[PDB]
Length: 359
Image 1: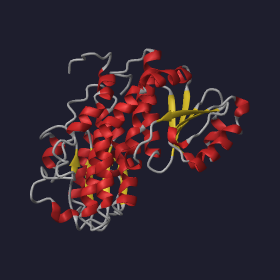
Image 2 (image 1 turned 180 degrees about the vertical axis):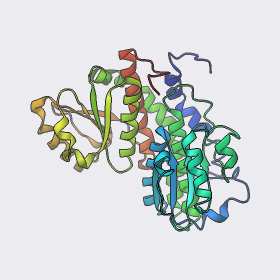
Image 3 (image 1 turned 45 degrees about the vertical axis):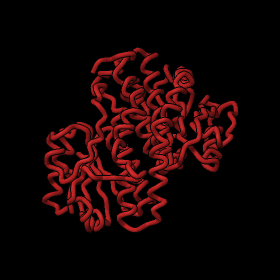
Image 4 (image 1 turned 90 degrees about the horizontal axis):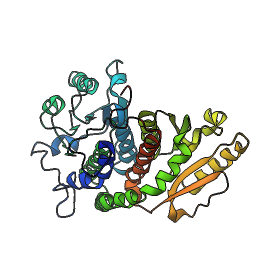
């Protein structure tokens, strides 16, 4: 990795995101559909007889996994369950009738997943689709089926592109399975549309850089933050929180937006800004009401929403507007501002973005 124009690998990776997402599509879309042809002819058996998915990873790879759960359950109608590699490999787990081992992972060497998988062999899982990003290495070698996200490599210790790409492949596989089960096949095409939209929708968001450099000032000297998502956006709060913990060292915690008032609200003052990710109007109405209950301790709500939704900043709710995007890929879109955000906080605090402390 040569740095080129950028200050850091991480910045670079963020800015490489649209491209990399190109590559993870190159020849997986043809006749404008999902071609899972590197899979080899022994692929499509199996996937048809699936009535449950089990995903299994660490770090950020886990959050990508968590996202794609929401997808399956609603889009492909296939039960999905997510687990942290370490939590898995030490419980007697009940197995699900006919189950797939999707094991998400970056470089596919990750100690914990690796043996997570192995335990499934002897637990009688239908088998193993790995998703990962390095050719032939220990996870790749022992998995039945591969889905190399080929990102070019990620040098910064904070997963950026690696997240988006994994989300993409997750997304194709949602499509492959939705057809291999009969359903509306429009439900494939939405994915495919959004899927092709995506690369330049991120460039949309990338251009918005500057406006995020602004907001990070609001965050650069805080020591707590509270990221709030719902449904499939919630796992994006986990990725939000995570990155802020990771590269800016702020205590960031993510939380189900519904749940503000069973715990955290009492934590909010001038030192814990609350970020929400992409609420709908009904949600926002509750959060608005929540945060007003704490205007006195000087708490602020920062909301990332569709310019299209016409929310308006009141004095202590601050709308950050993003462009419209197609619901199917929203989760992927919204990742980037949180990435840039964290990154800019890190930049202003001057903390070691590429190799951050203890990670």
